[PDB]
Amino acid sequence: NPEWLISEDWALLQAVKQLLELPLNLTIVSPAHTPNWDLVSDVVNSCSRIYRSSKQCRNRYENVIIPREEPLRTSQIYAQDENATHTQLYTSHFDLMKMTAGKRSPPINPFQKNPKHASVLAESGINYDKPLPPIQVASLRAERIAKEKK
Amino acid sequence: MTYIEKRFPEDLELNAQFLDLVNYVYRDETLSGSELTAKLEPAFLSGLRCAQPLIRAKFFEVFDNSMKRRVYERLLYVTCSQNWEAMGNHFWIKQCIELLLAVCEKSTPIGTSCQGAMLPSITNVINLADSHDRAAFAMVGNQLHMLTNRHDKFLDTLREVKTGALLSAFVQLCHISTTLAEKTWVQLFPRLWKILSDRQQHALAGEISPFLCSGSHQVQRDCQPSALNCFVEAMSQCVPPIPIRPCVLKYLGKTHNLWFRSTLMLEHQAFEKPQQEILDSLAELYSLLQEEDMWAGLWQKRCKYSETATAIAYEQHGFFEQAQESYEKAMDKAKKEHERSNASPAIFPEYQLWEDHWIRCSKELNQWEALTEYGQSKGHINPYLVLECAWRVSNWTAMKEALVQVEVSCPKEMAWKVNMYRGYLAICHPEEQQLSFIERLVEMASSLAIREWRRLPHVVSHVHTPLLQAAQQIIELQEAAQINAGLQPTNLGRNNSLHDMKTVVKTWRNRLPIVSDDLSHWSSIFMWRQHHYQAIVTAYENSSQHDPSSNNAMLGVHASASAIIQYGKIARKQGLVNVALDILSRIHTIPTVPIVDCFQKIRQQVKCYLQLAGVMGKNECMQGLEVIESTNLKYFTKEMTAEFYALKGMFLAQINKSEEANKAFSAAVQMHDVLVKAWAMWGDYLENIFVKERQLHLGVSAITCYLHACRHQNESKSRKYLAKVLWLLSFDDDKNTLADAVDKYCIGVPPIQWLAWIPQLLTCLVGSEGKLLLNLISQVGRVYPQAVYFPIRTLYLTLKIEQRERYKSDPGPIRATAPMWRCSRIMHMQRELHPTLLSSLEGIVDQMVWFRENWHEEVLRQLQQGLAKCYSVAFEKSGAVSDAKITPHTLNFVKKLVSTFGVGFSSAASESLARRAQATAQDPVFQKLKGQFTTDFDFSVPGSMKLHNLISKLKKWIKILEAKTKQLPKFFLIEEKCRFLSNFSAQTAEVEIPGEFLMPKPTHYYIKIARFMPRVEIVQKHNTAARRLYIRGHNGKIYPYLVMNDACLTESRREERVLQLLRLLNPCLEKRKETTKRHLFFTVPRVVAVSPQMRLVEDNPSSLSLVEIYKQRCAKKGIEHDNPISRYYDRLATVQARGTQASHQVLRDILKEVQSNMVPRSMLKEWALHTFPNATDYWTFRKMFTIQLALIGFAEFVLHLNRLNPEMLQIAQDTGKLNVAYFRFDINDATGDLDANRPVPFRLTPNISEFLTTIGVSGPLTASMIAVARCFAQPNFKVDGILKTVLRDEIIAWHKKTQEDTSGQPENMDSQQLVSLVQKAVTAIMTRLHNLAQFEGGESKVNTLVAAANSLDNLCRMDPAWHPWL
Amino acid sequence: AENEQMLKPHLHKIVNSSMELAQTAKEPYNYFLLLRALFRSIGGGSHDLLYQEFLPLLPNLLQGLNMLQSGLHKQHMKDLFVELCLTVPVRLSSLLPYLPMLMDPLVSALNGSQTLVSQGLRTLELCVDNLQPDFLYDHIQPVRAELMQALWRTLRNPADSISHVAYRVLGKFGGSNRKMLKESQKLHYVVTEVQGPSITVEFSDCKASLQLPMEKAIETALDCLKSANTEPYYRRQAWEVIKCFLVAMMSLEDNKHALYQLLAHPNFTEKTIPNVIISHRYKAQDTPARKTFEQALTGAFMSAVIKDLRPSALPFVASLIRHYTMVAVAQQCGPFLLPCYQVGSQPSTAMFHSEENGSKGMDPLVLIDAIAICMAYEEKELCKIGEVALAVIFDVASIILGSKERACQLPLFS
Ligand SMILES: O=P(O)(O)O[C@H]1[C@@H](OP(=O)(O)O)[C@@H](OP(=O)(O)O)[C@@H](OP(=O)(O)O)[C@@H](OP(=O)(O)O)[C@H]1OP(=O)(O)O
């Protein structure tokens, strides 16, 4: 799986912090406020990179956060360390790949009235040079229907 | 606790024993054991939710005593200290109801606070009336004494009932029923919140959100009535519940069945205005709801970079290539800005939008190779995109690696997607051909899809389209299973498997998705079919012995070619030519292909060239013509040559040559005279050259072409050609050449095709070309007697009524006119042919005449129309004087009204009704009323001629009459007077419901009237007391109808014409994308005119109007609905009192004050909120309202219809459909042309915009308007012909009306004036339609149109009677 | 082989006789059972001998079965009709000109019981597999909203196989499974703003009180008291709810001496009764309170029929009917006359409880509506309690007024 961005990591930390529970033991007084791992998962995968929020990752990366939170703190690494340069560089790479893909994509009066298209019609028995008015064509159709009926 | 209940659920004996054991453990010896209770919580909960009442009672009695008897303490307990995880898919909120109702006091008398519904006691009559009456009554056998004693004993027995007996039984009843108990919590929790003080409410609201999450309380995720759903509904239904996080709201909406409730809450937060998270979550949830329009509007409101708005506008209307280009430009500009300096983190959502929408666009544009190269990038592999776009290019190794990478991290919503991809892998992998687990994968995928379906709202919508599409590919995978099972060498060549393969291929060929689906799904289906088509082809190449006839490989080749051609056709229909050329270049790379499908490929190519030849260039069109001429025609058939020459003539008529095109059309029609399209296009070209050169020898030819094209084809297609035919009849000369032409070649055309145009040919029935049209209408009527009887009945009666006024000087009977005799001879012939059916129809019509009700509602409607006309004329005198005198016409109207005041075939029903009217006219009440009115309605006194004085007197009399007419019957039995209707039965005659033959249906299942229901109700609609008639059919369903008395034979006939126009335009909306995708359709009720004064219209019981809702809200507030107009006019008068003519600021401040004082813009919004308490129902109603309002606004703007007054708009509460009260073209009576140029294009008053919450307007409303504009703008539909055909008779009636005032020779208007006026009128609509259809640069004028529709600078100038505030 | 020759000559006879006789029979149930057995026997196996004689019977048989299943009938009768009309022993090859008559019962089978929905889905799959999609779509076009709505509702069925086959047939439909529905789906809505009846509950811990609406509660009570699947104790709880609702929605402010002095007046037995006519033709739409009252009254009348609830429901019902008729005769007769019952009055809305002014107090005439809806109930055993109610009304009216012929002039009887 792709590496975790510090932005989505701080987002996960805040989502866990917004569950009204402490990391010392994730079932605090008012035990009905058990940890909603699916909620923080939904809140995290809305970040820059791909979903990457299965049942495992949500617990694994929080258990990784706990040691380094109990070095710089996640909130400090978010406010510090080029706050928005990481996600912006990721998105710039994405846009560069987009442009490369879109660029390499493929771009995508000899009058000839040959005598074949007219010869087939002549063989069919109809004159092409002389346009038969629709009235005579209708009369011919009626005569053909009459012949068929007899 | 763990196993006894799992392995022995049915044997309730040991379960009850174990529950009694744990209850004893909890009850007795508590001082000794209190740690054991920790682990046995699931046992206690299960015993509490058991189905046995005694166990539940003994468990609740111990669960209640453990807590203080205080509502706040129990609420806090159940909200933060109690864990419901151990419950297990249970509706535990009923236990909350138990706990909250048990703490209530149950040692006091029972009572109720509903004083309005209190039942009076026996002795309550001792204090109601005055005193002395009862005082004298109080100072005034055994059979009665015993009764009184027993009754007093019984009453004493009742007074012993306490409130505790009610609550216990209420709770025991809520136990068994999950439904109607969720509602009890929803309705009781806010009541508890109301009594909680601020200190308690603050903490409770602050701790509810942790409880809304509550971690592992997710087993309810699959519960149909999930507990979190009810809890959040109740919490939101409170008054002060401000604090709730939008992220948790979106999570609950997605996971639990809270989609529409969550969206409503989020938008209610958003429209109250650190804070961008609300809009972010709302946009995410809208994109999750598949509601493209709302998402697009929200983002256009959020769009920072201008390129994003254009990209979203392009992608919203199917412009995928331009959308992709705009997205590329946008992200390039963003990359440049980033290289300049870092941007705020709030822009990341826009970047994700660009990413995913560029991915989607490239997916729609058949860029699978580019998508694979992108998702497979070394640094940022996107495994989901790769898994999606890998199998469509046969990259099975990449697909397998992406699958194994996704199966571990796939969203649970995409479980069925992962199953389908696993099946694709197992079926199509070269080195992993293991066809052992196939049906199991399909079963698991179907189960997961159904489980996801159970998580979606109950009202089907765009949210459910993904699963409805997935079903088809799942059943195809199931079929592919046996396909591959039969292609193996063990079964290869076997007839039993060959027949199954042939059948499955035929079914696939005959089973197709709909155009409303995106090209992505069409590709996902066709490419999946192509793999197995090729497998069939390849499988029959190494088994030359098996089936040695070169047929089964040809079968697969033909299947693949047909699938490719169908995919290209679908891509073309959606508006993609480049992908069409790509697919054509693809299909060209085959060793050999059939000759039948190559002709269809060439046909699709020439169709692409056709639809691309709108602004064709010389070079490109000549190259296309050369490519056309380069095709060989040696091994082809004959009819294909006819179609080819027809398309050639079309493409060359597109260019301004017109000679070789005529030759090619003639040659094609001679090659195959049965080819309908060729002859239709030839007739189109002939009509064009006739209208241009005006040669008589061409009109007959054009009409013959149209008729021969309409002969052998379906009516849906032939409609626009009959339209062209009917319009050409306005060019005939004195010799009536084209008349005899159409009369000579009409034998052969189906008679059903003329049903949709009976009114058009009836107007020509009165012209100099009569006799032949009479013969034709009689011939077509021999098959449909009623469809021709009703219209001729109405027209004959109208002609008789008109002649009665033309011969005012001659008393008694008079000689009939030529059209009268002409249309009555046909009725005589019909009665001779269909005597029973016509006699039953006559009986029905003569019985419904009894619906002439009385003088009360008659004079009420008369004075209502009088007040309406008074206001309409006063608006004209508003700005000038506003102290104006009544006009002569209005004076004559009111005089005639107050003089008649209600009393104004050889049949006997009319005579009996007149006798009854003269009889009931002998009472003194109505005589005294007439006297009092005449002593006031006289105008011969000074000071009463003022228009506003008349308006005030009319309002006074309106109030008096409405207070008088409130005591009348509301329904009557049909058997009282209508004997033939009550005695009507299916055995009498096979008569169909009125309005059935109007639109022909493919099937002949026409519901016949089984019998008329006995009850006939009276409903106040259209400012009149209409009579509602119910008719039942042989299917058991009931249809309601209103027998409306027009009282105006011209306005009703001009009104029911736009209904026919819309009904003709409705099919077209259903034949294009971006219209079916949005479910755009006109709601056109059925209206049939049975007589000049009466017409029968279809309706539904629950259909209010805007004015009805307004007056209902006013009565609720206790005010008069006529207050705002009177206030506007009072301000106008007081401003003009000092000579100053009211300026613009005057109107603006008047509107502002009347809106802020007595007409708040939030009236319709609160009305809708109260009407629809359910979030899903409210959302569906609002969406239907938005789309229907947009459609009718587009109609009333493009089509020059009268202003949509508020009382006209009918609003169906049961579906949300919006239909108006009979629009009509506002043709200028003076000039005779359409001049629909009001300040406001369509009704978008502040109340509506507030109901549409200001984003339904910017999104679905304008989106639907643009879609319907671009839809009708397509030339293939030829809506101009229908418009011309309708405007022909719309203007003929205008000319007839204008010439009647002065004074056969005058029976015909003119040979050149009528056509010129019709052409002038139709262009005014066509230009307005094209102006709206223009969508250059991702921008449209519809935005400026909707912006002007609600601008106060223009609304203030509208008519007060138009209610610019409602 | 041998018995098909003796049944063929009588097939048309028995079919037509059972069809024309059950129409005017006393218990037209065994005839439909016989028809179902005959259809099952003819369909079992490939006889190919009775098929020729049964073919000319579909034109009238199918029409009759459709007319039967379309009309209002008891649940079991409707189920039998829809199941015997769908399972016809005729191949689809010959049912083409008579296929349109099978969609109306199909949409009802899809909405019927588990067996009925299963049979309907079976027939739907049979017809979609054995026929071209285009013709089948043109066939279902008249009725598409109901069919699709039922197919979407049954998708949420608890039965796994039922939902699975529903999804399978929906996928078999193809793109037509999501085409635009002109007959848009219906959605629930409220018609009035006035609040329905409620019970007052108090809280002594916070010195406050609440209002408990009980419209849907009374609805649930009536629903669970009507159905036969409910258990006895739940029926008893619903009866208790209805009883407390009835007793809580009245004044209960009557005295013994005051009642005796009120009913013991010469005017009640000497003064002429005003001959005004009561007619629901002037009655407005039912308000929430009135419909809840009707539901409670019919639930009480039903409990009076329930065997285990009769001992306590019948006496309470009789006494409540006595109360209602006594208050009615007291308000519409005697020296005290309401402004709408005086001499010369005419029918008006003042007699009924409506959202408008109407009457001053709750309309006691609602008792007649309850008896009417009870006697018109699907079960005929309820007519007994309606007759008992009418009997006690007439008896107590004649008692309070004497001269039985005189107590019939009351507008209550009108
Ligand atoms: O479906 P296609 O082959 O692409 O062409 C169709 C077809 O007309 P033709 O098949 O004769 O070209 C339609 O009618 P059906 O045959 O499907 O019934 C219909 O044409 P009508 O308007 O005559 O119904 C439609 O046209 P539209 O886009 O106006 O709905 C469209 O023709 P196009 O080539 O214009 O798509």
Image (cartoon, coloured by chain):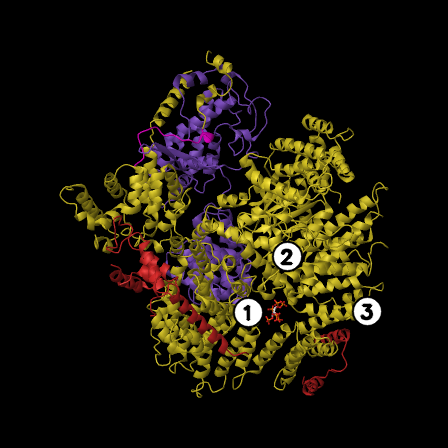
Chain colours: A red, B yellow, C purple
**Mark 1 is on which residue type?**
Gln
Tags 3 and 2 touching, CB below 8 Å: no
Queried whether the magenta region covers residue B114, the answer comes back as: yes
Instruction: Please say whether residue C23 is visible from this viewpoint.
Output: yes
Residue shown at 73% from the left, 29% from the top:
B934
**Within-10-Å neighbours for mark 1: few <14, some 14–19, many 20+:** some
Label 1 beta carbon less than 8 Å to ligand 1:
no
Which residues make up the magenta segment?
B103-118
Secondary structure type for disc 1: helix
Q: Which residue is mark 3?
A: B696
Q: Which residue is mark 2?
A: B1063
Determine the residue located farthest toward the top in the rendered image. Answer: B139
Q: Position of residue C357 (x, y in %)?
A: 54, 30
Of the two numbered discs 2 and 1 in the rendering, the one whose residue sits closer to the viewer: 1
Residue B661 higher or lower than B1062, as above or below: below
**Mark 2 is on which residue type?**
Arg
Point out the image quarter for the N terminus of chain C: bottom left
Seen in the image, is B981 located left or right of residue B1315? left
Q: Position of residue B388 (x, y in %)?
A: 42, 71
Q: Position of residue C218 (x, y in %)?
A: 40, 39
